[PDB]
Image (cartoon, grey):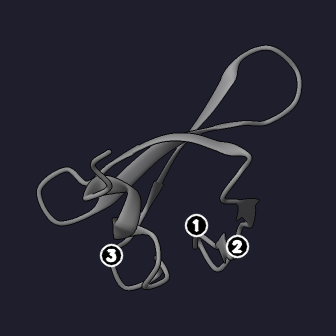
């Protein structure tokens, strides 16, 4: 599965494996995906824009 964001009509895309951490703050949702250079590319996607299999990691306990 993959998650897509939405910044000013700019639907972004990042593989779930490319992502690193994910934590929903208040109502929106944020995370840290590795762009591919050296600086972590943080991102703030919305709750409706996030798929349904994304909160899974937030409630994934081993």
Q: Position of residue 24 (x, y in %)?
A: 25, 54
What label does residue 47 carry, if any? 3
Local crowd size for mark 3, using a 10 Å CA cut-off: few (<14), some (14–19), many (≥20)? some
Residue at 73% in and 59% down: 14
Give left or right: position of 23 versus 57. left
Toward the viewer: 33 or 55? 55
The quadrant of the rendering that contains the C terminus is: top left
Cα separation between marks 1 and 3: 13 Å
Residue 37 vertical position relative to residue 29 in the rendered view, above or below: above
When the figure is inspected, residue 2 is found, relative to residue 59, above or below; the finding is below
Residue 62 is marked as none
Task: Where is residue 15? Give x, y as percent.
Answer: 74, 60
> For mark 2, does the 10 Å Cα neighbourhood hold few (<14), some (14 to 19), or many (20 or more) residues?
few
Q: Name the secondary structure under disc 1.
A: loop
Asked which secondary structure carries label 2, the reply is loop
Using the numbered discs, state the Cα–Cα distance from disc 1 to disc 2 in whole angstroms.
5 Å
Residue depicted at 87% across the width and 30% down the height: 36
* Mark sitting earlier along the chain (1/3): 1
The mark that comes first in sequence, 2 or 3, is: 2
**34 sits to left or right of 27:** right
CB atoms at circles 1 and 2 under 8 Å apart? yes
Q: Which residue shows up at 66% across the image and 59% down it? A: 16
- Disc number at residue 10? 2
Mark 3 lies on a secondary structure that is loop
Q: In the orientation shown, which residue stands out farthest toward the right?
A: 37
Dot 1 corresponds to which residue? 7
Q: CA distance from mark 2 to mark 3?
A: 16 Å
Circle 2 or circle 3, nearest the eye? 3
Q: Residues within 10 Å of mark 1 (few under 14, many from 20)?
A: few
Q: Give the camera-side residue of 10 and 27.
A: 27
Task: Say whether residue 5 is left or right of residue 17.
Answer: left
- The image quadrant of residue 54 is bottom left
């Amino acid at each position: 599965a993959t998650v897509k964001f939405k910044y000013k009509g700019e639907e972004k895309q990042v593989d779930i494996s490319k992502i690193k951490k994910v934590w929903r703050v208040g109502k929106m949702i944020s995370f840290t995906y590795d762009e591919g250079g050296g600086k972590t590319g943080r991102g703030a996607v919305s709750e409706k824009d996030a798929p349904k299999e994304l909160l899974q990691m937030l409630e994934k306990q081993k």
